[PDB]
Image: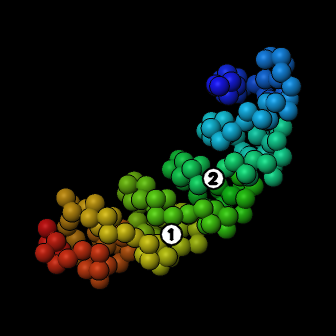
């Protein structure tokens, strides 16, 4: 019922799926049958590349790309990784990381003080697409600290033109 828990502790110990089969007396294929999504994130938290995990758990690079989803994209974008930086860790193309992007991946960077042009070059291939996908909540997130001509709009793109389509005029000066 929870045998997958008695396997994620040997992974964080440094052992490999080959050694997890011997220590637990089981077979190597059965260890591959207990490797889930949760057992992969912990190995993208020690900096290990996906190709390293291809030789840690013995799974194919085709079979590790099955498990890695948008969740690790947020985690790596959070740390300090960028555009091509993430793509090399996971063997994916940068476009595959573009196909795993969203507004939630952008909020965390507004929640670390970055600007539109700052994140446009961090995640790569972004310019007005960031401005296209800056939500009202991000401008509403700063309603407690509204205080510029266009820098509460430069962090979020441009000028009051943006802070007029994403909020009213009574809250332009609020």
- Mark number, residue 4: none
- Crowding at dot 2, Cα within 10 Å, few <14 / some 14-19 / many 20+, comes out as few
Q: CA distance from mark 1 to mark 2?
A: 22 Å
Label 1: element kind: helix
The front one of 25 and 147 is 25
- Mark 1 or 2, closer to the camera: 2
- For residue 109, side relative to residue 15 (left or right): left
Q: How many marks?
A: 2
Q: Provide the residue designation for mark 2.
A: 69
Q: Position of residue 8 (x, y in %)?
A: 66, 27
- For residue 89, side relative to residue 27 (left or right): left
Which quadrant holds residue 38? top right
Q: Quadrant of the N terminus?
A: top right
Q: Which residue shows up at 84% across the image and 46% down it?
A: 60
Q: Position of residue 47 (x, y in %)?
A: 65, 40
Q: Which residue shows up at 75% across the image and 55% down it?
A: 91
Q: Position of residue 12 (x, y in %)?
A: 66, 27
> Mark 1 or 2 closer to N-term?
2
Q: Which residue shows up at 79% across the image and 30% down it?
A: 31
Q: Quadrant of the C terminus?
A: bottom left
Q: Provide the residue designation for mark 1.
A: 120
Q: Position of residue 65 (x, y in %)?
A: 74, 52
Dots 1 and 2: beta carbons under 8 Å? no
- For residue 31, side relative to residue 161 (left or right): right
The front one of 28 and 104 is 28
- Crowding at dot 1, Cα within 10 Å, few <14 / some 14-19 / many 20+, comes out as some
């Amino acid at each position: 019922e929870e045998l997958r828990r008695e396997v994620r502790e040997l992974i964080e110990e440094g052992k490999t799926a080959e050694e997890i089969a011997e220590i637990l007396g089981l077979s190597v294929d059965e260890i591959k049958e207990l490797i889930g999504r949760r057992e992969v994130r912990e190995l993208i938290e020690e900096g290990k590349t996906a190709e390293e995990i291809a030789e840690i758990l013995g799974l194919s690079v085709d079979e590790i790309k099955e498990l890695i989803g948008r969740r690790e994209v947020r985690e790596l974008i959070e740390e300090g990784k960028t555009a091509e930086e993430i793509a090399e860790i996971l063997g994916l193309s940068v476009d595959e990381i573009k196909e795993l992007i969203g507004r939630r991946e952008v909020r965390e960077l507004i929640e670390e003080g970055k600007t539109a042009e700052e994140i446009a070059e961090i995640l790569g291939l972004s310019v007005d697409e960031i401005k296209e996908l800056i939500g009202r909540r991000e401008v509403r997130e700063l309603i407690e600290e509204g205080k510029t001509a266009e820098e509460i709009a430069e962090i979020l793109g441009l000028s009051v033109d943006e802070i007029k389509e994403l909020i009213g005029e009574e809250e332009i000066k609020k």
